[PDB]
Image (spheres, helix red, strand yellow):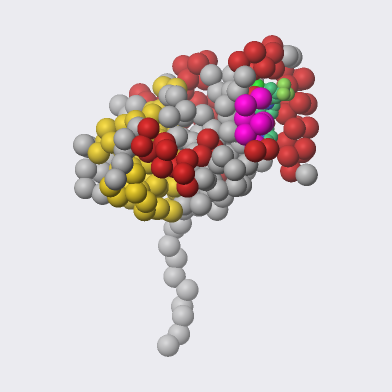
Amino acid sequence: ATLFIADLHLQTEEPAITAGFLRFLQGEARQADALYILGDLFEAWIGDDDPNPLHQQIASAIKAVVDAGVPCYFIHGNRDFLVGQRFARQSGMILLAEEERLDLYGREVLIMHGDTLCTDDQGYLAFRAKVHTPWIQRLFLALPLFIRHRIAARMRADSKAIMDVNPQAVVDAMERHHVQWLIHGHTHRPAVHELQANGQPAWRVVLGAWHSEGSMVKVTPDDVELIHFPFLEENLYFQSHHH
Ligand SMILES: CC(=O)N1CCc2cc(S(=O)(=O)N3CCN(c4cc(C(F)(F)F)cc(Cl)n4)CC3)ccc21
Ligand SMILES: [Mn+2]
Ligand SMILES: [Mn+2]
């Protein structure tokens, strides 16, 4: 089986999500044929030289999955688009493009983060075009770390003071790649949408964000599974209910 996760939005202020991800990496992920992380692994990223200890803890845990024989892949999200080759080397992850076509046990599957499908949010698309401009990225990454931190903290507060996908963009993407299956995240609306692409039925599978519990897509030769699970091992106990 091949696993897909996304939108964990890991951050030191949310240690429960981190604990749930580490348990996932130590258990479920060790049995997979491959693990794909479709963006927004971290709530924020300002460059691979960031000494944030969470980054090294996550890198080491993913690297242990890679060392256990499970190749791990990463497509950038809108939050962590600055994840680069240094962190890829530290984690053992392979960085992929914003769109990839996979062959999963015979079925062709398109994967992406999903933010490029929200073509109706012109405000976000302007921000995305800005921070994806290569000379702007190089200029920001050259700034001192403490300056990048203050910029990011202010820009996050400015944003606090998610649009769904455009149906035709979905069709266009699935017909550009000639697939009947699409997996993405970003929208935080886990679902399986049926549609038509290339004159045949097609399905758009959406991952969930790790807010209260975990979420993953498991692809087997026989089916596609959208699975919700708790962060930690909920040890069962009994309460003496009465008839
Ligand atoms: C919609 C959405 O995705 N948002 C909204 C706010 C936000 C904040 C983050 S951030 O905190 O992780 N971080 C902020 C600073 N940033 C910059 C800043 C610059 C510039 F300052 F020079 F312009 C250039 C570049 Cl290349 N990167 C890197 C990322 C991530 C995603 C989002
Ligand atoms: Mn997200
Ligand atoms: Mn996103």
Q: Residue at x 22, y 37 (%)?
A: 105
Residue drawn where x is 43% and y is 62% of the image = 236
**Which quarter shows the N terminus?**
top left
The percent coordinates of residue 56 (x first, y second) are 55, 25
Q: Return the residue nearer the eye: 116 or 225.
A: 116
Instruction: Tell whether position 3 is magenta.
Output: no
Q: Nearer the viewer, residue 164 or 215?
A: 164
| Any part of residue 1 in sight | yes
Picture quadrant of residue 74: top left
- Residue reaching furthest to the front: 199
Name which residue lies at 36% across and 53% down: 194
The segment highlighted magenta reads: 124-130
**In the rendering, at what x and y percent does residue 117 appear?**
51, 39
Q: Position of residue 21 (x, y in %)?
A: 48, 40
Say if residue 60 shows up in the picture.
Answer: no
Looking at the image, residue 40 lies above or below residue 88: below
Asked if 99 appears above or below 180 in the picture, the reply is above
Quadrant in the picture for the C terminus: bottom left
Looking at the image, residue 163 sits to the left or right of residue 35; the answer is: right
